[PDB]
Length: 94
Image (cartoon, rainbow, N blue to C red):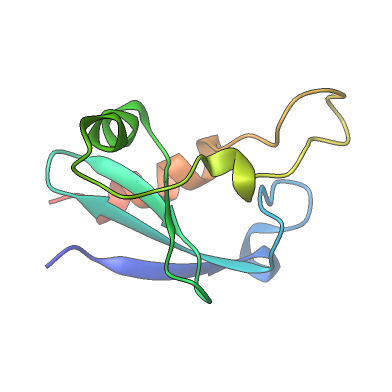
């Protein structure tokens, strides 16, 4: 079954943490579709392009990642980068 893990701002650090909550869940589905999962509501948000097309497909019920992705205080007008989390989830792939 897809591996799901919990990551925390404590582990990643405030400087790179990219979400409006202190813990989120990461997974990698068959096809290398990466998603972030909300631990209280279980809603999924696409992390990479493959996942965005699964959503766009109608195959996966999910919301835009911008719903929980926070702005970058060091890059005004832009969102905090997902690359630290994409690199963590890509390692759950199989």
